[PDB]
Image (cartoon, rainbow over all chains, first blue to last red; front, side, top):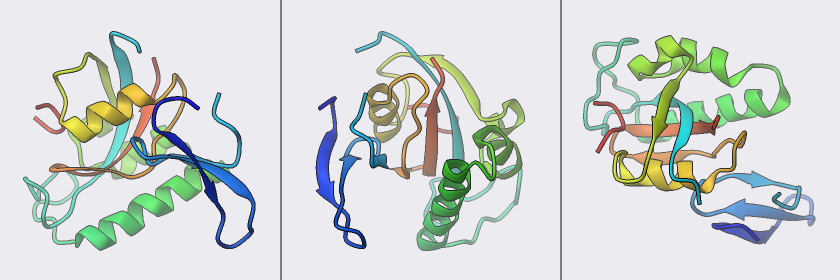
Length: 145
Length: 5
């Protein structure tokens, strides 16, 4: 399997699935390095974030646990097709990149906070991460290039 | 600046 991917067992259904311990992605389907990647992200900050403030709210008071619940909800809506990643990033990302539908542009290794870099480089083009924790908060990352 | 090292 590709970097980070492992086989796992559904607790509710008993069917095999695949989990990536670098990106926190999970999926039923068997999974399908670059010098630079282009990613978008959706950030949900919390009270332990290095800077608990964003364009959305001056004092961010939600707990890490609450942030993770919000991230999980956004992932659910994205995966069901109820909402687009770009639309959720524009509305709800605690990063100024929200104004560009979450797009960060292209970057190489040795530029981003480490969990974010590692997730970004382990995604294939078009793939989305699970919840990725950094000192910034919790991210959903979409690799676009 | 945001998730930049």
